[PDB]
Length: 52
Length: 234
Ligand SMILES: O=C1[C@@H](NS(=O)(=O)c2ccc3cc(Cl)ccc3c2)CCN1c1ccc2c(c1F)CCNC2
Ligand SMILES: [Ca+2]
Ligand SMILES: [Mg+2]
Image (cartoon, rainbow over all chains, first blue to last red; front, side):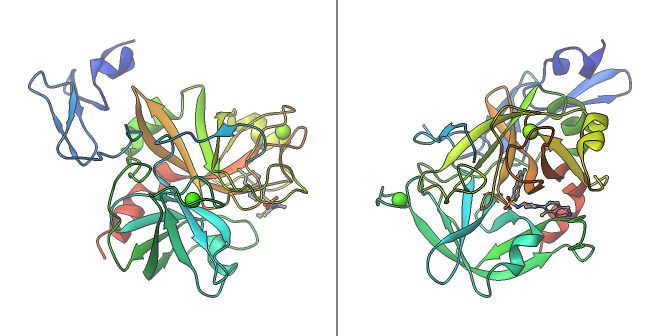
């Protein structure tokens, strides 16, 4: 298990392997956090979250 | 939904219900955005004129979250085949935008490769709807959800008296009495990942409901990600 194969590459959401390194990204309505892994909602009612 | 549980408050906010002229649900849908609903192409032959209802968990009481939306455009997959239900997918553009609130929120569209490698390899997905609670029963007045295991593609092909195209996948159980059913068609099959729910399928068809040696057959949403994106730009 390597990169995206190992625990989703530590990404909250999408994991891609560009070169031989993990690249994380997020669904629309989320921005990648400063650590380059977590996905932060841009606004209220982001997709995929149960309400409250 | 045969078996499973009630969707509790806020639990299935992406659920949409296609309602006929008599305000009766005949199919489900998934909220993709303020303007778009994902559903099954086969649902578009079950009613002449229909609307979409969101924010509803109990069709017998007003809960304060219900909203009815008229449909501006029906975008059906042109390769949809009634005999096989291949390409069983459609997108609906609503006339007015859905206002997200408690019990009303979209499910996320995943990326194809990641979904196939990471979501579809999870043990289970979640199917939801107002469909029948047993094969010969009536439709549920309560929105239900059900955890459905992903089923091995070969086992599913072996179990099916009908072709399973590249655009379908199977989920549910061999013998356990849990499955989607009549009226759940067009509805969400979502997969949970780190408390985030991604749409992975569309309730398509089954040889009855919850029958032994039979599984639920769902449109493989990941095969249609580019198509959905195109349909959502017009
Ligand atoms: O979908 C259903 C059944 N209708 S249902 O309302 O009971 C129904 C509809 C959708 C379902 C979806 C899932 Cl995931 C599970 C059970 C379902 C059950 C009756 C027979 N049937 C069916 C069987 C085989 C085939 C098709 C069917 F519709 C279409 C494509 N060709 C094969
Ligand atoms: Ca209600
Ligand atoms: Mg079965």
